[PDB]
Length: 117
Image (cartoon, rainbow, N blue to C red; front, side):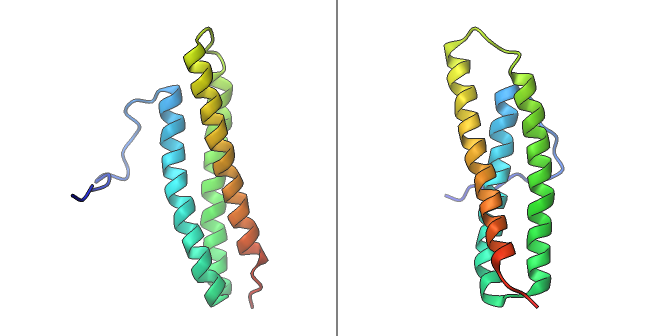
């Protein structure tokens, strides 16, 4: 009926596999992106400077950690080869990650676009 989330937030990655990390990061990113993006909508109504600051600050810190791990992971996972499936999956991960990063800076564009006091 109702799917409870992950009870332990400070839980370390169990699988820790190249593609597993990628799908793990994007799952977290997706959830936080949609979260802050809905907050953008609220911010857009409040036009609150402090709210703007919190939103852009949390966006920034998550965007940075995501990009750092993504860049690292991409470089590493590239050591894998000879596998039509892995090729497809890698390319697919790159596809979704790029979309995710786009949406981050897109939301960034929105928060920076709202004039505050």
